Image 1 (cartoon, rainbow over the protein chains, first blue to last red):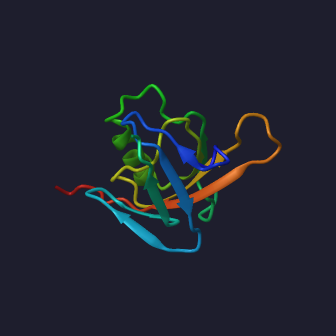
Image 2 (cartoon, rainbow over the protein chains, first blue to last red):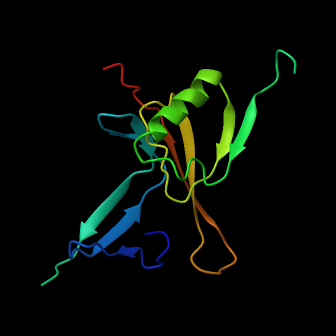
Length: 49
Length: 82
């Protein structure tokens, strides 16, 4: 997303995705392996219709 | 060296050529020795449970522009005693 100035992204699933970033945050993204601390984000998906 | 020497190493395109699975072992070997390291990699992500802790940075520079954009993370891992 940061590469494209419009912060738009494309995916093989047919979903256009827009990424907005807030960077003041200690948020944890948890999984079976490790807890990744990163800046929060939001992902919108456009209407491919 | 002395008692206080920080064991520093570096790696470029780190561990490229190792299979996607076994890269887990390498970071275990590194941790056991206690190295402080600065690595880089085009595809690797450092999200491996064997890592006791690890800072990350992603460098973005679109094609030729004269600026570099840096995103920061951190990882702590859950080395699998299972």
